[PDB]
Image (cartoon, rainbow, N blue to C red; front, side, top):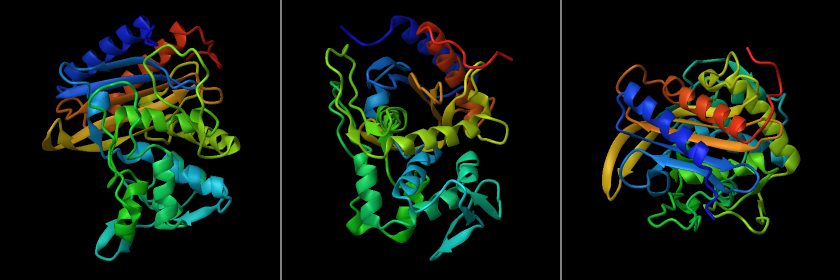
Length: 324
């Protein structure tokens, strides 16, 4: 009566182990969720504790879809609105992008995973509004998944923030989530704006979602996220032949390791497919890759690609375009 699919579990295990070996990494995790039920289809970690649930990270770029979603959901901005995306200062701190563009529209802000653009979208909202939104996504909240040692992550009280904290949170630093929490948050995008509960038991009753954004917003955001896995986006290494995939990739930071402090870079890739009508969310982390790549997409993209493609094949979902 587990919801896990042995074929997907085996696939995830094999692909994770391949990447951890190739990149000479310290650890890794893969989570596969049913995109419309929140059931866990696979959950694998390298040997030791259940890092998917026990270990929180500052997620980095994989958090960026959420402020964009909030901004669109509010009606304050449109996907065609253009922002100045030059580096800027908040007191002595600088917010800047990997690759600098003078302006981007909201589509471009998603496509390029712009720190500046994402932070300016967040900046249209008060600290309380942003906090309440992250809380509604489950940040800092117990999932009660049935696993012991389940991290709640960290969402600092907005009443204590600074303008720089709100900005960094929008691009995934200064809040913390486990990989399972991150996969769960993506159900807002896949399940037409409603956050699903997570479970490893086969469901008997349809889960009740909690509305966070409009279904129309979720649909638009999924469309925007496809650009991340096409030429010009950071997540091209995770593209899946025969499908459109909405995803994000980035370098996360791990500040806690079990019951001890840590400081490690973590390569991350999270996405869903088919993008228009998603069946699966696949989330991958690889801790401290030391070989054949540091850049997050190169390290975790291939795992995501193989696990997503394999999962869709296992579940019988037909490609939506011819294979290349």
